[PDB]
Length: 286
Length: 294
Ligand SMILES: Nc1ncc(C(=O)NC2CN(C(=O)C3CC3)C2)c2ccc(-c3cccc(F)c3)nc12
Ligand SMILES: [Mg+2]
Image (cartoon, rainbow over all chains, first blue to last red; front, side, top):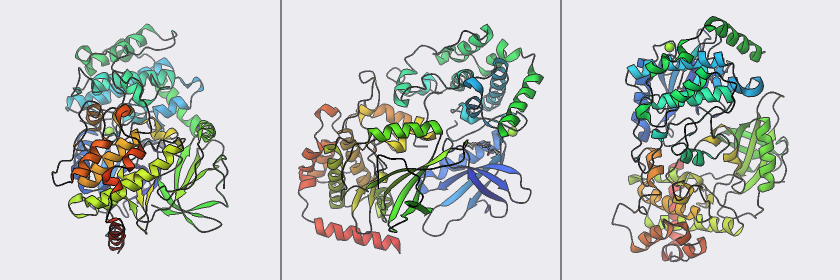
């Protein structure tokens, strides 16, 4: 029981060409300031799958590494169709880190850039985990950048609806099997996803990308922990990947333990990397 | 009109209004209504389409298939993702999901289920004899026309262009209509796609027409995907249904695809073959379309 978005917000275009679904690049009518709008048709069979998606965005978006919730609206539809719920949040102008690697020579980021982004993801995850919230969808597409290289987490669509989605970033425990019938979920599942995102930043695609999603979903709980293809990477980076990709979630380190990892903790070029990333955004824009 | 080419849609087809989204189109020359699926494809994805166009199997028009007219690409500037247009026949009454939802108790009459299922099977029979698996049989992909004609969705099902390219290609979609064999397990490491997979999907669509939703709807898609290859064949909740209907469901939902009947064998099933109210049901469905429209 909110208000109509008319004169307050307006849709411009669909952002991720399908990746995020019905997510638009919106505009605050009065100021002209950009915002991202998630549009979801409120049906009788989706009444509480939308109500608590608003409650999660408002409460947990108050953190520098999470895209801030602005407000929720309802655009009333004529008698013969369902109403549209508009979920407004801060817009991230630089795009996703999947798009960043895709628009880089050799489809690979500098090891210190991976260290900066991964730390910011972990910092965002730490805020959610302390608040008893699992993201459940950490992937390069759900990790966004702003015009001044700020890293922000997005999508609470599956956080703790009938489609399974991309499997490549899923942790083994997330995928139900014979010895894991109920797929015992944990906050540490996001850390496996964070490690796959680091391989994604280092190679331009997640492990098993060249496979059918159904075969990848079958192999993730059977295959040994994924490794980086190239030997060029530092011993600190291999240790971080190893740390994130522990097959059994029961002996996988916590977000706090991973924040203390030398690859995340020891960042001497922090300022220089932030400028290097800011330069890369401008160069791609023009 | 060509299916083996990748022409610009200019002068051939034009978009009219909103209905990978499907938009109401038109044939520039005749004015004939069309359903156009518009997808933003990268330069590399355009080459995948050129390959898959060669993978297309040729087959005639059919009374129970919304005719696929071809694929086109509307060129965007060098750097921007071009638009892939997949043109198909227009069905004014909408999907079966829309029909069962806009019906009291979210259930169709057993004879209506018998008529629709037979028309799905007839459409599937034409594709199967032409070595083509539909791969996405469900209520939402089974359409009705103003004249209460049942037609299957076809945006090049032979090459699966509407599912190979785009952002949602790497996504595992809705699992509820999937046959056990299309889901990978320990003694099925590689998902085997047989023509009979559509028949399991057809049987799940019959449960969808009878109950409003497919079996295991009340579950997380990941748990449903896990249970489909383990759970015994799904059954109808209500005992009200005829012995012919239970037998048809049983016939469609044979766990092992190797032991599942063919489309021809299922067309000879008493629930499909014996239809005395065929004309009356056709009128009943035509009446239902008109009263929903007003
Ligand atoms: N908050 C967001 N800001 C920017 C973009 C995005 O895609 N931005 C790129 C497209 N870009 C532009 O249009 C440039 C010109 C400014 C950058 C963006 C994309 C997806 C989502 C998202 C997904 C699922 C759920 C959800 F609640 C939010 N949220 C956002
Ligand atoms: Mg914030």
